[PDB]
Amino acid sequence: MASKMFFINDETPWEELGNGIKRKVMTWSDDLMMVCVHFDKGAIGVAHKHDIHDQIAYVAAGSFEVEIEGQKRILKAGDAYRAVKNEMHGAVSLEDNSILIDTFNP
Amino acid sequence: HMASKMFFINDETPWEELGNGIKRKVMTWSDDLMMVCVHFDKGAIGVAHKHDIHDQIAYVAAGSFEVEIEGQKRILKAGDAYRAVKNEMHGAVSLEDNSILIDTFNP
Amino acid sequence: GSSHHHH
Amino acid sequence: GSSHHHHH
Ligand code: NI
Ligand code: NI
């Protein structure tokens, strides 16, 4: 679909990803993309790295244990984390209805 | 001169007052990406402006806003977002206290 | 992203 | 940003 000027969350369905994770691609341009990622308690964002882009994610709701290149913090709503290209990063949700807003430059 | 953060912990980071009902926190950044929290009292105005060379995508973390981009206007609430690509005029008006936009852009 | 899925 | 301000 076309990118949105205005993303209205409650008008937009979830895309189910399996294993307690679902998402909404919110909007994007050539240079930026924003995605809402929703986690059940215990859902795991499997550790991975991106060769060619950076990622900053905002904790919109709930809480997570986030591990980045072997450093690990518990983050709650209002917090954020940075993973630059080639840094391994993953997240474990600590409660239902936990949400990360991921931003990156694809 | 302050180094960018791997982990931004909101309640450990003070606000930078900007005046006129607006305060912010630069949260973290890389060479390619930056994230800033902007907090508005009711009626505070993000004056309409544009960026020549970079895009912007903003998340409504809390509260609500009237957002106007290139003459189109919507009321956004927590969970919503908006896009303003380079050279697009955009501005916002807070509709309630403690309304927060998480701005992302390519610095 | 914060999960390992891409688009 | 969502406000007019720049960050030097
Ligand atoms: Ni990632
Ligand atoms: Ni702007």
Image (cartoon, coloured by chain):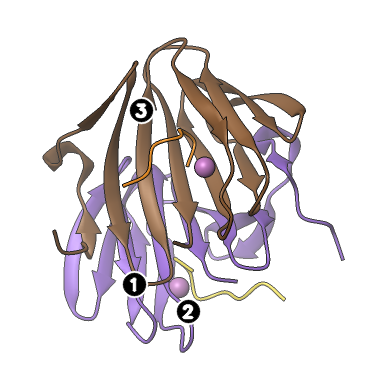
Chain colours: A brown, B purple, C orange, D yellow
Chain for numbered disc 3: A
Between disc 1 and disc 2, the foreground one is 2
Real-space Cα distance between discs 3 and 1?
A: 25 Å
Q: Residues within 10 Å of mark 2 (few under 14, many from 20)?
A: some
Real-space Cα distance between discs 2 and 3?
A: 28 Å
* Residue at x-position 22% and y-position 65%: A5
Give yes or no for contact between labels 3 and 1 (Cβ–Cβ under 8 Å): no
Q: As rendered, which of A79 and B46 lies closer to the eye? A: A79
Real-space Cα distance between discs 1 and 2?
A: 9 Å
Residue with the mark numbered 2: B54
Q: Residue furthest right?
A: B1
Do marks 2 and 3 share a subunit? no
SS type, badge 1: strand
In percent of width and height, residue D2 lies at: 44, 65
> In the rendered image of this protein, does residue A56 appear above or below residue B51?
above
Residue with the mark numbered 3: A38
What is the three-letter code of the residue carrying label 2? His
Q: Residues within 10 Å of mark 1 (few under 14, many from 20)?
A: many
- Evaluate whether residue C7 shows in this view: yes
